[PDB]
Image (cartoon, rainbow, N blue to C red; front, side, top):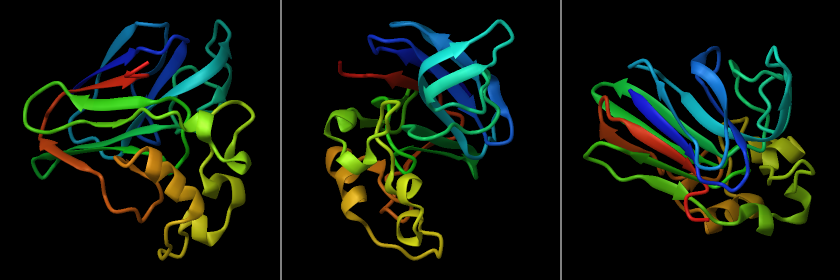
Length: 207
C-alpha cells in the first residue's frame, strides 16, 4: 500500500512511520511546509503508525532530538515515538479488510487528517486546537498536550487492569475530537476499508 504524507502546517515537521519493532519504508523524513512524501507499506502490516515530530535537530548521521515524538534520537524511526503524539494507526489486509483510526491515547501534538485515496470508506480527522485548549496539568513544555496516562501513571488512566472508565482528561480529547480514541477502552472509531486501499495523511488539514 501507498501512503502520501503531506505537511500543510506552516512549520516544518519530521514525519515518522513504524510498526513498533521496525521502520516502515525509510522510517522518517523532513517535510517543509507543503512537501509531500510517499511511502510503500508492505501488505499485511499489523499496527503501523504514522506521526509527526516537531522542533527536531539532526546531524549528518541522522542522530538528534525532537521536542515531540522523538524515536530514540533517530531521523529514521524504528521504534514508536515519545508522547505527545497524535497517531495515525492502521492494520492492513486483515482477512481482506483494512482498519484505520486516529488516536489521542498517547496525546496530541499536530492536527491530522487520515483519509483513503481509493474508494469505499470515509476518512477521519482531528483538527481542533487541542494544544491551545490543553488543561494546565496536561501541557507538555516541549509543545503539545499529553494524555493523562503519560502524566500520572495510574491504572485508571492507563487501563492496565483491562477495566477503566472515561476520565475528566479523556473527556477533553473526546469533546474536541470525537473521531479519535480518547482512552484505550473508548468506543471504537476505527474505520473499515477495502483491503489494499491507499491513503493520505495530512498534517494541519484546515489551517
